[PDB]
Amino acid sequence: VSRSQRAGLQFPVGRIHRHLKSRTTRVGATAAVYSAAILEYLTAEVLELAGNASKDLKVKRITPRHLQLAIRGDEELDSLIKATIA
Amino acid sequence: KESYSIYVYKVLKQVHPDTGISSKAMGIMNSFVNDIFERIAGEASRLAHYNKRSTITSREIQTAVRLLLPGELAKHAVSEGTKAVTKYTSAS
Amino acid sequence: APRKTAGNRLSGLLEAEEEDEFYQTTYGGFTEESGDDEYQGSDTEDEVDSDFDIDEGSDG
């Protein structure tokens, strides 16, 4: 069915393919599928940690402080965001 | 610049189906995803030029991921990426 | 004579402050704010371009 469904992804491989084309001005399907999977994985990792931080609250909702706990609290995520900004 | 917030939300449903996210926190997630993607895409372009590849494929993405992602993030991301590509190139 | 440890924690402290500032400024700051509404989730379509499934592809 959907190309993102074919890859088993929630992130949109067509949109990411166009984004890659825009930022690399040929982009194969596998580049877009792999990029989507990678962005989805990093997203899942940050949200898992952030949502763990927001457990124990009756209304479970991730705020910027939970994202801070998730990324700043994690040697790899913290170095990734620092390199990325700088 | 690009909007991935709705896909971030779907991933959140997967990892924590009872958990919401605030608008500002979602904005931070969208910003981070966009910046990480820009880095991967720039690196992949540089790798394809360096290796004289006419087309950016998952080989260049994977090398960029290894170069850019700290430690175990890279390992797990490479696993996930390879998995997705296998699924995409198989039948369904 | 001066002691050796004098001020030997100052640069760690400055690095900690710099990291504080980094998380208070990056992406608008990793800080809670009054009026921060819940993100309300409006799904979208994902169409691939014509050149999505392109063909992607020594002796001695």
Image: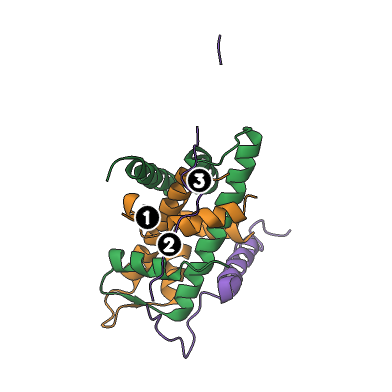
Disc 2 residue type (three-letter): Asp
Chain identifier for the green-coloured part of the image: B
Whole-angstrom CA distance, mark 1 to mark 3, is 20 Å
Compared across the picture, whether A66 is left or right of A6 comes to right
Query: In this picture, is C5 found above or below B44?
Result: below
The N terminus of chain A lies in which quarter of the figure?
bottom left
Which lettered chain is shown in orange?
Answer: A
Are there few (<14), some (14-19), or many (20+) residues within 10 Å of tag 3? many
| Residue A79 can be seen, yes or no | no
Neighbours of disc 1 within 10 Å: few (<14), some (14-19), many (20+): many
Circle 1: element type: helix
The residue positioned 54% from the left and 56% from the top of the image is A18
Looking at the image, the residue that sits furthest to the top is C60
- Labels 1, 2: one chain: no
Q: Can you give x and y, in whole percent of width and height, for residue A84 in the image? A: 58, 58
Q: Colour of chain C?
A: purple
Q: Which mark is residue A4?
A: 1
Query: In this rendering, is residue B54 above or below A17?
Result: above
**Residue B85 image-quadrant placement:** top left
x and y, in percent, of residue C43 in the image: 38, 72
Q: Are marks 1 and 3 on the same chain?
A: no
Give the mark toward the camera: 3 or 2.
2
Q: What residue is disc 3 on?
A: B65
**Looking at the picture, does residue A77 appear above or below residue B47?**
below
Quadrant of the image occupied by residue C4: bottom right
Between residue C52 and residue B75, name the one nearer to us: C52
Q: Amino acid at mark 1?
A: Ser
Q: Are marks 1 and 2 in contact (CB under 8 Å)?
A: yes
Q: Which dot marks residue C46? A: 2
